[PDB]
Amino acid sequence: SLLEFGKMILEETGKLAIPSYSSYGCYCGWGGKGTPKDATDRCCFVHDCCYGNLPDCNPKSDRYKYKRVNGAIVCEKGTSCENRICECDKAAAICFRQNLNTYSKKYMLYPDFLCKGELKC
Ligand SMILES: CN1c2ccccc2[C@]23C[C@H]4[C@H]([C@@H]5C[C@H](O)N4[C@@H](C5)[C@H]12)[C@H]3O
Image 1 (cartoon, rainbow, N blue to C red):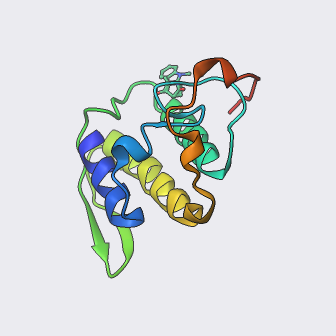
Image 2: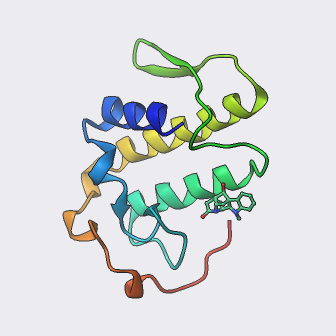
């Protein structure tokens, strides 16, 4: 759920998912249109796609458990949905951490009309 995801992000990047990741570019946060603006936005695109592979799960509200073995994220065993949701989130958190160097404040609160294009998962 958003509770685990938000905490994962904070731990990984040091940034508060809200508002650092919840209104960035074309895919980070409400939204799903156009060409991703940068690496961080691509992380959110892939994340969106990952959740898209789970039509009968509920990623925003289904809670999972995860632990950290030193710095590594390890998804704990739960229902099939919880395991798969956790893997989606873990990947996004790592992706965000891998692209912190290019994270740009100019993409925060990015206006909708500038999100143009088609990009299939
Ligand atoms: C296609 N679509 C869906 C079709 C059928 C079930 C679920 C989904 C979506 C809605 C949502 C979300 C991501 C994000 C995304 O932008 N949308 C996609 C993938 C999904 C994902 O959970």
